[PDB]
Length: 99
Length: 99
Ligand SMILES: CC(C)(C)NC(=O)[C@@H]1CN(Cc2cccnc2)CCN1C[C@@H](O)C[C@@H](Cc1ccccc1)C(=O)N[C@H]1c2ccccc2C[C@H]1O
Image (cartoon, rainbow over all chains, first blue to last red; front, side, top):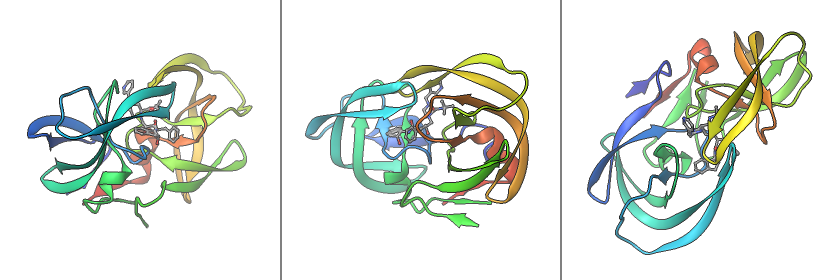
């Protein structure tokens, strides 16, 4: 689709077989999802944004459906304020900015 | 133009008589520019990122050119590691996400 930016660009995702709402975030290098049970192995990491750093669980090679499009890649899980789809997965679904 | 997401989507902006590099950020509600001595009145604000909140100065009706496209709107100034162009100004230049 073509998505305008008058409202937050929220989409439905499926991760670990569960549906969630997430923000398409071109300013995010990575994808970070709120705390959940997720099948796979993980390693601890820290990520930083406005306001500082948070501790997350890094899961690699996770299947995630984003607005009906498949991606398979790195998903961080931790105390993010909103679910965020970052560039690592937006590139996989072919998303670009246009103006 | 079209901007892919393999790398951070940085563009040149003009604000306050200065050229800067800034990130086109669909996840940002607001526009946040690194500390600079902009003239006139402002209002204190706090804004929340992934790691918590920071204190910024809110300036209204600030002219800013984004990749050659003029816009005018609210600009927040404060200690950010990156200049962020948020939705409030991206809408004004007709930016969309497409996939
Ligand atoms: C107005 C303001 C800019 C404060 N908004 C944000 O920070 C929002 C906050 N919401 C949350 C919110 C908070 C409070 C209220 N409403 C919403 C989550 C999404 N962010 C937008 C992010 O796109 C901002 C970028 C800024 C940044 C870019 C590069 C380097 C440093 C900072 C951001 O935090 N990006 C980081 C990021 C993000 C996710 C995963 C990994 C990484 C690394 C890094 O790329």
